[PDB]
Length: 6
Length: 252
Length: 29
Ligand SMILES: *[C@@H]1O[C@H](CO)[C@@H](O)[C@H](O)[C@H]1NC(C)=O
Ligand SMILES: OC[C@H]1O[C@@H](O)[C@H](O)[C@@H](O)[C@@H]1O
Ligand code: NA
Ligand code: NA
Image (cartoon, rainbow over the protein chains, first blue to last red):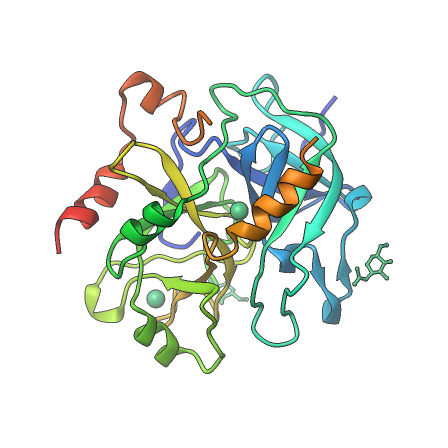
């Protein structure tokens, strides 16, 4: 699982 | 990276993560060679037998990173690409000859404690440093082994191996556009790039001027860290004329 | 043109933990 930006 | 260790903060500030927009995933490594251009391996982008053919709209690059999965607020940048350029004589049919590609950012990236490009070499720096036994450095978020994935950028220092040894240990046709590197069984020490490391940099530090130069790009190997086998790397100086030709006309 | 000098290392006269092994390989042998 990859942590999201913005 | 196999038998490496954690990168230190800021150790490899040109290191770039090639990133698929959807599904989200880590594709390759890559490197920052100026505020406008990232350098990578062609088989990262185009490999027709596995239906690989990523256009610019498909990818993002993440620069400044340390952790593999975390969003590193206030440290990393993310950029859309403007265009991809693969070497026109890239040979995927056989041996991955000329396994290089350029990627142009849409916007110039700002440099910082974590984002800084690396040098490409000149003929002299090439001659001097590309020698059997001289060591360089590979960085990557690739597989730890042949768990699994590292938590942070991994680093290993590896010796360049003499052409005959490289040639005599694979049954694939080596071209002068490749070099190989890694330790031999009788040298004890271990270490290799792995899946996920493809496209990332093999750097050397010049003792003439103290700058890091990218002599290679992770291209391929058979398994990872196997005795009697070696990592193959794309000879960057050999292909430097294509690199400049591309930049001068699309650097804008 | 400032290529390859790291802000956290070379620009402040700090070495990383393993670059010396790079240089040990250029001088030894
Ligand atoms: C790869 O993608 C391009 C651009 O969408 C497409 O036109 C082509 O058929 C594909 N094959 C290539 C570039 O070899
Ligand atoms: O499936 C392939 C890989 O699985 C892993 O669990 C092992 O540690 C690797 O060395 C092996 O080659
Ligand atoms: Na690279
Ligand atoms: Na090996």
